[PDB]
Length: 266
Image 1: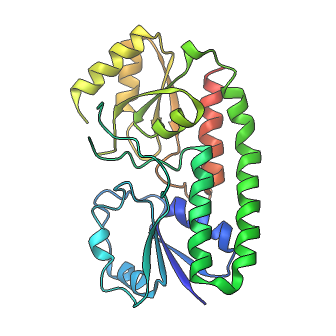
Image 2: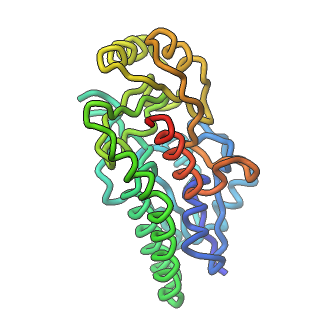
């Protein structure tokens, strides 16, 4: 049985849905851990050796631990599952890519398709199954998320702002035609951006700001006060929740966070 290692929780869940136990899917950065300076353990090095295929996000999400993906099993490739996705930079201009591409309905289809392509190249005798599984999963995602999008699109163009703590929704904003405001581009803080956000909020009379599940709510709350906006609560973007939590799968993560956003905009 072939082994496929996913760099983190969201990618392993996607892969599990496409492969459905035709391969053994593993995860390096498990739910509740962040990729920025994640400590690759000894046990993780075994996962790395056992991999026949390794699936990364790219967009520099894995930058601090890519160096552990060496001395690999002969023939094991590293696939970046965000191929074909036009990156969004972390600056205002030439800058580092924002990694949060999976927070998008369109992109979910690209992750899935890239992962299907690679599983099929790895294990061609099961091609017909990956193809079926991938279509079903895509439909499944679309069915759960399109109604949320449809409702989001009923907002008038002046009132469409995704304000967060981390710049986690820049791709959703582009996918759905919103603009995104936030405090810092990636978890790991500056006063100028806080100042900028407060100004933009006031000018566009923005009513809500969110924090997220792997960061502090203190800044969002403080900015809510300073703008006379409301704190919108916690979104799930950077990691799947633990199994009792509200976002234990990729589909559930998309659904929970877009649901929370849409219920806040209405």
